[PDB]
Image (tube, rainbow over all chains, first blue to last red; front, top):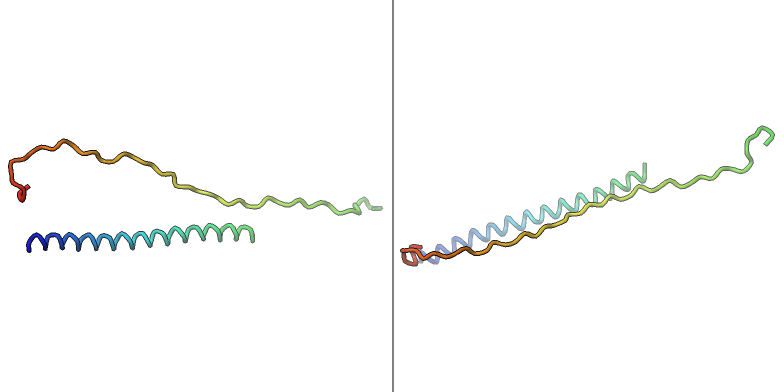
Length: 49
Length: 48
């Protein structure tokens, strides 16, 4: 039971870390796509000026 | 004309369009960690 509780506590740690990694990944991809479309809008605004 | 102004109008050349700036992320590739030499200790398997 001590060995099993060890392994399951390590698995809890890995699941928490995987959750944090995938939400950081999603926020990073969001910021990247925001910068790309901001660049395109800046080009269009220069063409308007 | 009589006043020296031209009858035929002038040519209007097209200005250059603003270009789109490009960036890139070049990537590297370093080697992995290679395994060192193993030493045998004095304790049993649950202790080590």
